[PDB]
Length: 121
Image (cartoon, rainbow, N blue to C red; front, side, top):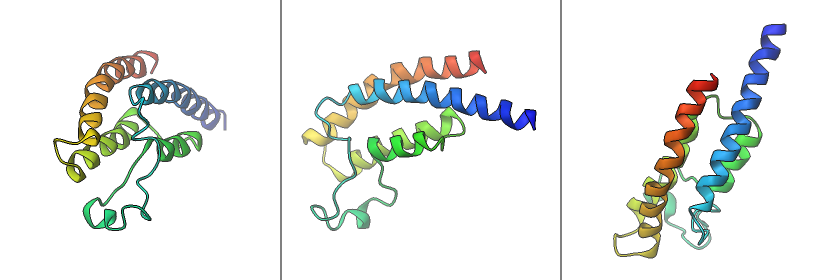
């Protein structure tokens, strides 16, 4: 149908906007602490602590399969990156601190993303 195509074009354009958002958030992680999944070879107990691991490469895979239907789903995944880290790592660690800085800096980007998603529909 023509409607299915129109819906698909909307999803494609959301994917375009989310790709730009993801790039801007990942720039706020210059140490690449959140770039890849936590290694279960190096942290063998991780899944005993964290039930839904997340990282920027995993988000990118979902994004490129057009797997985010809306901004809320994408933000859920970004929040998991931060929240998982702040639980597993203590306050005095470079990992925790990196997450706080990512959260604070990402808030600005996500604030305008939400306006753009609503604005452009």
